[PDB]
Length: 236
Length: 193
Ligand SMILES: *[C@@H]1O[C@H](CO[C@@H]2O[C@@H](C)[C@@H](O)[C@@H](O)[C@@H]2O)[C@@H](O[C@@H]2O[C@H](CO)[C@@H](O[C@@H]3O[C@H](CO)[C@@H](O)[C@H](O)[C@@H]3O)[C@H](O)[C@H]2NC(C)=O)[C@H](O[C@@H]2O[C@@H](C)[C@@H](O)[C@@H](O)[C@@H]2O)[C@H]1NC(C)=O
Image (cartoon, rainbow over all chains, first blue to last red; front, side, top):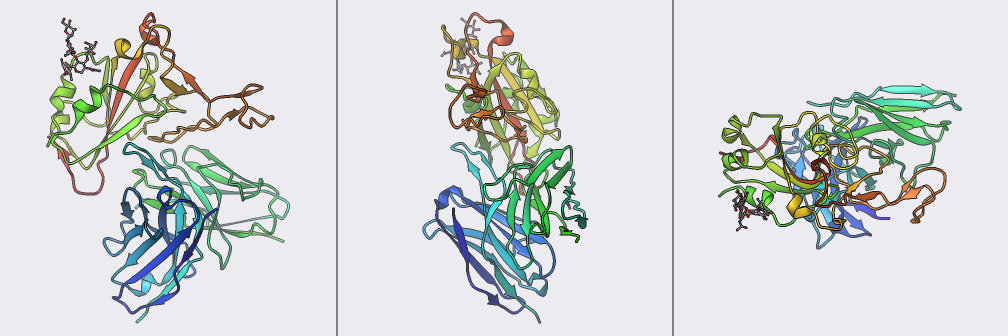
């Protein structure tokens, strides 16, 4: 049970630089790893980079060549993400989320997926591998809905699902291809076959109406990637 | 200056296959003659690249994974294979770039009366993905009764001990396995001949 309170909103002109900091309270900081996702206004989730503080290892998405640099201060138990050469396209909400990781005493680490998200930070400025996700599926209020997610790297890497209700930070409801978190209710189920993964909701409610994104990593595992998105609205 | 291949192979201690050690090697010139042209290598297969041209190849990063298994299990280490090891212990992708090297270790890792210091994972509820390692001891729940830390009654401890002895057939004898993977990342290259 660990919470994250990111810093307040910022405004900058094109070409400026923004620093966003999410303090993580509870637990032990050296045990965790952190990553950064940006939500373009009205568009899907977009991953930037992650960091493992105790080993000081960080990798960023290739679209941000050297603009973004991630760091953290174990002394202060905070994570810093800093963007430079700002542009209008960078206008988005920036989320900081805790990645549940595994770090070995020999040089082994495996990353897994983001379970705890921050409140969010909105920043405004103005002056090759993809997961294919069906854009929208509708289902009847007593029935069951199946949402797919298909990339050619899915036997090699795990998949994770996050539930983003409108005006809300994402919530992980299914992890490690098909695992059940303590919070999400029993109705949520996952399954993987070949290069296909499906999310399964048993007797879907109207409660369970939100965008769903499937996050998985590169074939190499170096970069994570996000699905285009899926709007599940339960038809009346 | 040189990659520590001698430290990896000729080591006093080897880990069990479920807790397989991984050592990241980087920023070192690699002489593959010693590894390629060495005696007593029961198995030595390279899938991604040729061992002849291996010495002159150049990569971003190279990892050396090393562990101990039985003799009948050496065949499972190849890519796209299945078993109680290839699924619950140590898995390689089908885009494997690298080599697998094994040798007979019956003198070192077999004690008279049974070596119960070497284990493998027997039961698990899901295949792991390649290059993933699970050290957990959480009990495998086979059915309705929740285990709740108590074994028996359709609940077992999930790791089994190899139980090596000197008076065993070669297939049931321990073997020392070293897997070499070449990361070839989109970054500056650091190791080659
Ligand atoms: C680690 O290395 C030691 C030195 O061996 C040398 O380095 C390694 C990296 C490799 O290149 C070897 O080819 C080199 O020789 C090992 O101890 C030496 O092992 C050699 C055999 O490799 C052994 O020679 C024996 O000589 C008899 C002749 O009477 C011959 O019939 C045998 O077949 C064998 O060739 C040396 O006596 C020995 N030297 C010393 C100082 O101990 C070491 O362990 C050994 O390796 C195997 C072959 C068995 O001899 C084991 O009982 C012994 O522990 C290497 N491995 C480990 C885990 O320590």
